[PDB]
Amino acid sequence: MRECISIHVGQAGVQIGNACWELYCLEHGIQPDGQMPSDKTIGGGDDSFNTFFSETGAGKHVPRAVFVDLEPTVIDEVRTGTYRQLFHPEQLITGKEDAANNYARGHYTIGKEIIDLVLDRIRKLADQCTGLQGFSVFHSFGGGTGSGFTSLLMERLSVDYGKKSKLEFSIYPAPQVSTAVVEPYNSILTTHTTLEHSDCAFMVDNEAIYDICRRNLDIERPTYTNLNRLIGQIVSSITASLRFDGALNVDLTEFQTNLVPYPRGHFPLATYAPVISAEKAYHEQLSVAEITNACFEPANQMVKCDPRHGKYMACCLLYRGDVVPKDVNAAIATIKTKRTIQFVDWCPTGFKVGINYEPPTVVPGGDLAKVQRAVCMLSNTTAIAEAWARLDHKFDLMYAKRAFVHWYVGEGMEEGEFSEAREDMAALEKDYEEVGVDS
Amino acid sequence: KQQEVIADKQMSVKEDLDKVEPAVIEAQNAVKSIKKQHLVEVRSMANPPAAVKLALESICLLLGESTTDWKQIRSIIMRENFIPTIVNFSAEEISDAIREKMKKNYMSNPSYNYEIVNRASLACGPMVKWAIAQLNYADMLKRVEPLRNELQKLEDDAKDNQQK
Amino acid sequence: MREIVHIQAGQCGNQIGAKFWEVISDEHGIDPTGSYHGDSDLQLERINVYYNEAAGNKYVPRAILVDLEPGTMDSVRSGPFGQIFRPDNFVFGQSGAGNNWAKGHYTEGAELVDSVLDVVRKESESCDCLQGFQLTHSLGGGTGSGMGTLLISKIREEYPDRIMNTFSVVPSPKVSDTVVEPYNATLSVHQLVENTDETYCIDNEALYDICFRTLKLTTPTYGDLNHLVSATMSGVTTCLRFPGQLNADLRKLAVNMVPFPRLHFFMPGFAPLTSRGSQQYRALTVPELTQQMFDAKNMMAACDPRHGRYLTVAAVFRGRMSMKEVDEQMLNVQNKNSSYFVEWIPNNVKTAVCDIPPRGLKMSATFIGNSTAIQELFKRISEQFTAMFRRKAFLHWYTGEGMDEMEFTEAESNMNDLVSEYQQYQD
């Protein structure tokens, strides 16, 4: 109650965060400075004067997230137009880049230089953890700061402040799907660090959305800016539904304990229904069965474990928007009673679901628009040996032909660490295989 | 007969040297046959793993330099006279208090073990392998030295008694 | 800010830096008079790439204006874009274009390098924003070769920690026979690769090819061919300092240029154009751009590396386009080439893109490819030697300038190892 503090690291994690901020700002009708003319309109939070009045308020407005970026362009963008009093100039953060796609680079090389100033803001952010609940960290996981800086921070969060829940939203392709043969090499250690120190990760495949953005949504010019705008709509459809209005308004803790019922984090792939060309050009309101069916359209469901297979533990559908109770129970009962889909034989139950009842009130402009019926989906497969098995395979597919661990050690890390982490992924394969054939 | 003592002592010095000498030959050959990328691998690092630092300070202190400083020790492998110094190394010239200080800092040390260093960096591997064999060879050569000099005194007496 | 200082060595090496000056300045809002003309975002920040601000908004060089001789200095100062500011930023003394490699390394280089190195010494530690040094170098006489190899060696001994980029203007690498050059040239090349970090190589006679075919001009003026290269150079340096999530800096550019590090040569080619500098249509779209990247006849350096293995490609774009279209068109042309980049790594091209277009151009880009499979060049310098290595009437000239016979022996060894290396990398 309401939502809770949000940490935005990396350039994707800031543009996603700006997209989400515009969504909260747009439904609200917030004035750029002031002084605001409504009694009172909900949007971020349930006051809107003095602006933002985001649960945090006063002075020169105290912000409810932190953005950290390489270029002044975003600080110029907020200082000149709207959002200007909705942030504070000393917590709108701007630095520089020098870039490497290497684990050792964020862990050591820039990681020992820029740490103490950002640390001091992390220490203060952990002192003033508004909303009470935990840390929402927007990643930044695949690169050299993504791999390196996140691995150092994840431990430091976890050892000092492990009583708090850590929610990590991650943009990253499932292994071997990327054209890059050298892309697993920096990611092998973070993948290993995640084993110990990540209980909760919601993952988007950037390759899956690229294909959806080009073909389902029928966008002529995809670019990064437009993709990150679309993944802000995901983050908003989830979060902005559970903040405080017409919903179950499920807590961070309550969700985490449903996600993770036994040792090692239970990370699902995220998908989203109205990333469809009819919807973008405006079409029918839809019934809860039909929004389901739009969501279960080709390309929108994953092909990873093969579409109907991989032995689902559960799928969890998050029904935003006005809903009828008959319609929703049949919406999740129909797939099960069809029984096209494959589940674990010990547990064919699938009772996992979010039903909420506030509509999106956002104005036409972006790829989201004002609607009655929405859904988002988290898919959990047991037979994930295939992911680990690809990570294992793809590293050696360079490696056997010619050795290529040199650069990841030339930036300052131990040699044996890389391949031991690889060996771990290979033993993980058979652990997630056996649960993938269940009992 | 006269040669009996000379022969004994000579074989005695050689039995000691042969235990360590195929290692020194294997180790010089290790350092010669490196590809030029594995000098850049050990050099590039801004913040080195600690075993890398310990092997690069070890060889630098053995070989010719007084520098503990990461900025100065990493470039010494790109000198044009590095292999000339190693091919024309004199392990005898290395002074006795200093030898035992080197074995104390590097040889005895936990993270200077050959398995812990090649785990850290195989590109440190060739360089640590010379540093170990050499520093051990100066130690065994100096240890056989009192009997090596008594040999060259006996050889000198043995020639002079022959010219008598 | 970047504040890059450009060192310019030998007569074509300055000529190309000259021609850069007049393009980069216009672009970034600096007048012929040194006064303002901007009112665009790079005609405001970005602009401190080569310049600094003073005097009611008149612009002082961070990359100072320098030559050796007064009338050639006079041409740099007459400009149009050398007329900028007050006389402390014009420097000259000595001359160059001497003769004999062994004489140029020792006796004549000793005097020249002292006057030149002392310029840099004051400048180097007085630029605290320096994100790097840019070096346009040519081979003119004994000064651009043997003096020049000393120079690179002497400068990289003073500054091993400072970032360096060498663009080399080279007459087409070893075409037709030579007399007593082959020892001298493999000694120069053996000094090149131990004194050089990052090497881009420009071929004159690939320029002549593109002039007669693409440009459709039958007089191939080299001032104009440098003025075209400068326009493309501008295209690179300015692009990586615009917004755009595929753009990249220092260690990410570096690891990409040499994924296996022993120094290798880097090869310019062309992107969209069916013409430049003449003809109404001069091309702008995603197939036009890629077409020339997957040809073979635009690229620099007469040594044909592409038959042996194609090797890694850096591509740098400026202009509005579908990010996704280029990646679909790149999936097309990379499976015309297949796993023929190297066995070890299928697909081997990485791009860097910005939305904001160039000066009067709508879209343009560059190709910078990579050295594999070039033993043919290192065998061709040895093969052109034999008849004159037998007859040998002119290497006494050289050895009698201070040059020892054993440095030539070592050099032939190094040429033989370089034959090796390329052959190894082809397998």
Image (spheres, rainbow, N blue to C red):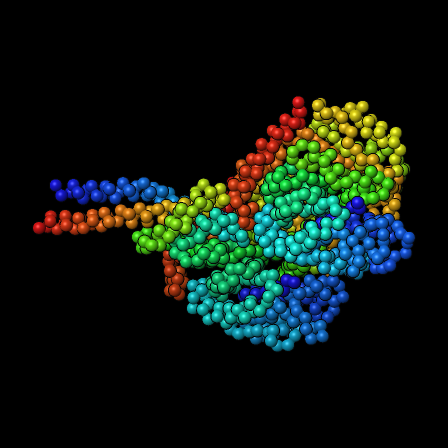
Splitting the image into 4 quarters, where does residue C35 fall?
A: bottom right
Which quarter of the figure is the N terminus of chain C placed in?
bottom right
Q: Is residue C217 above or below residue B37?
A: below
x 23%, y 41%: residue: B11
Q: Is residue B136 above or below residue A69?
A: above
In depth, the one of C45 and A253 nearer the eye is: A253
Q: Quadrant of residue B8?
A: top left
**Total tally of numbered discs in the picture:** 0
* Residue C152 percent coordinates (x, y): 50, 62
Nearer to the camera, A23 or A282: A23
How far across and down, in percent of the image, does residue A422 sit?
A: 57, 37
Residue ID at (59%, 74%): C90
Q: Is residue C96 visible?
A: no
Please, which residue is most extreme toward the left here?
B164
Left or right: where does residue A375 sit relative to residue A152? Answer: right
Look at 17% across and 43% down and name the residue there. Answer: B5
